[PDB]
Image (cartoon, grey):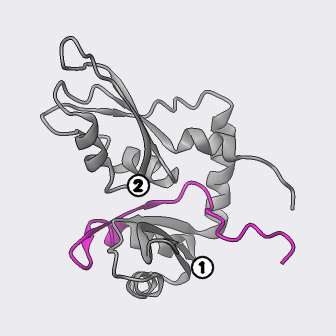
Amino acid sequence: GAMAQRQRALAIMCRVYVGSIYYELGEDTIRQAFAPFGPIKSIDMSWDSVTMKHKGFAFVEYEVPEAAQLALEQMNSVMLGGRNIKVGRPSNIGQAQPIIDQLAEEARAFNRIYVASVHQDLSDDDIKSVFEAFGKIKSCTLARDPTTGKHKGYGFIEYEKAQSSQDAVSSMNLFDLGGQYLRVGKAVTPPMPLLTPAT
């Protein structure tokens, strides 16, 4: 049971602070450019209505924190136009840091990774099948929704070996599987599909 709430810090981890961006990119296009990492649930975008441009920052909040840490991980280079963007400001100072670090350790215990841009037609087992070809997998769980008829486009995979899961991250990253580039990254917190502590 435990009932130790870490989800408050996760609500922070689901967000990525994107700084600078570029004086051009709008809210809708930014959603499209960050979607590769995960489905964006909310965006706080800087927009000045008198100049019709913006030089500031924006908060990209995904459903899962993985895509946020992941978008930070891979895309801390540029974001269109020609600007070195800043993703996140986790200067290892704060109350959330210890929590993030703890769950990081918890993700290590599960040997779990995150995969995005998972082609709509490919099911959990198929993603496991190909990743299994590189590392010894333990479990496959795509974010699948009963009221869509398919999976939402992102998922998570968990290995029996923390080494093997990192192999998949390197090999399967930007792998075209079904006409889509699987975005793979390290899972920062264990996504519990069945939170049933009495089963």
Q: Tell me which label, 2 or 1, sits earlier in the chain.
A: 2
Which amino acid is tagged 2?
Answer: Pro
Q: Which residue is mark 1?
A: 160
Numbered range of the magenta stretch: 170-199
Tell me, yes or no, if residue 93 can be seen here. yes
Magenta run includes residue 33: no
Residue at 77% over, 47% down: 5
Residue at 64% over, 28% down: 94
Which amino acid is tagged 1?
Answer: Glu
Numbered disc 1: secondary structure = loop
> In this image, 74 relative to 59: left or right?
left
Q: Residues within 10 Å of mark 2 (few under 14, many from 20)?
A: many
Q: Are marks 2 and 1 in contact (CB under 8 Å)?
A: no
Q: Which residue is mark 2?
A: 39
- Distance from label 2 to label 1 (Cα)? 27 Å
Q: How many marks?
A: 2
Image position, residue 6 (x, y; %):
71, 46
Image position, residue 159 (x, y; %):
55, 76
Residue extending farthest left: 81
Image position, residue 11 (x, y; %):
59, 42
**Between 173 and 142, the one nearer to me in the picture:** 142
